[PDB]
Image: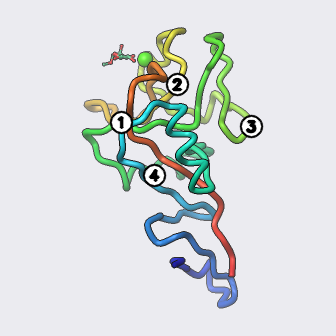
Amino acid sequence: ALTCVMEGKDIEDWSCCPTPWTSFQSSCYFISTGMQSWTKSQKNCSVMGADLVVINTREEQDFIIQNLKRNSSYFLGLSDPGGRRHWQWVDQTPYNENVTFWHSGEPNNLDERCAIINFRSSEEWGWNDIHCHVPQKSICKMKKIYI
Ligand SMILES: CO[C@H]1O[C@H](CO)[C@@H](O)[C@H](O)[C@@H]1O
Ligand SMILES: [Ca+2]
C-alpha cells in the first residue's frame, strides 16, 4: 500500500511512499534498524528500490533526525573509497563542502572511508567518518511516487 499526501493546496498533486516509509518534500525515507556494513546497507537500500540517504540541505537533515534515535548511528550514502578525501554520494550528485554537517573535528581519518550520522553531546546531530566494515543502522532514500 501507498501513503499519499497533498502537495500544497493543489487537490491533484498527491505524492506517495510505501507505508513503512516517511515523507519529506519530494522524497521517501526508510530507517533500516538492522546492523550491516556500508556496502551491505547500500545493497539493502537498492533491493527496496532506493539508495543510502543523500543529504542536500539542512532542512532535509532536520527532517531526517526526527525519525532517528539519539543513541544510534546511521550510515549515509557518503564515502571516500580511495582515502583521498574525495567524497562521493551514492547517487552521483555533487559533494558540496559548505552544505555538510560533520561534527567538530570530523572527518578525521583517511582510513575511515564511510560516513554516519549520529548524536554527540551539545553538538547534537552531525556526521562522522567511520570504518565501512563496522555494522550500523542505515537510512534509505528514494523519490516519491505520484498517482
Ligand atoms: C568515538 O569517536 C571517536 O572514535 C571514532 C571511531 O570509533 C572516530 O570515528 C571518531 O572520529 C572519534 O575519534
Ligand atoms: Ca571519524
**Separation of disc 1 and disc 3 at Cα?**
23 Å
**Separation of disc 1 and disc 2 at Cα?**
12 Å
Are dots 1 and 3 in contact, CB under 8 Å? no
Residue drawn at (63%, 81%) of the image: 14
* Residue, far bottom: 11
The correct choice, above or below, for 9 with respect to 107 in the image is below
Pick whichever of labels 1 and 3 is earlier in the sequence: 1
Q: Position of residue 7 (x, y in %)?
A: 62, 77
User: Which residue position is annotated with label 2?
Assistant: 114
How many neighbours does mark 4 have within 10 angstroms: few (below 14), some (14-19), or many (20 or more)? some
Q: Which mark is residue 92?
A: 3
Q: Quadrant of residue 143?
A: bottom right
Three-letter code for the amino acid on which mark 3 is drawn? Gln
Secondary element under disc 2, as helix, strand or loop, is strand
Are dots 3 and 4 in contact, CB under 8 Å? no
Pick whichever of labels 3 and 4 is earlier in the sequence: 4
Q: Position of residue 40 (x, y in %)?
A: 51, 36
Q: Position of residue 55 (x, y in %)?
A: 58, 43
Pick whichever of labels 2 and 3 is earlier in the sequence: 3
- The residue mark sitting in front, 3 or 4, is 3
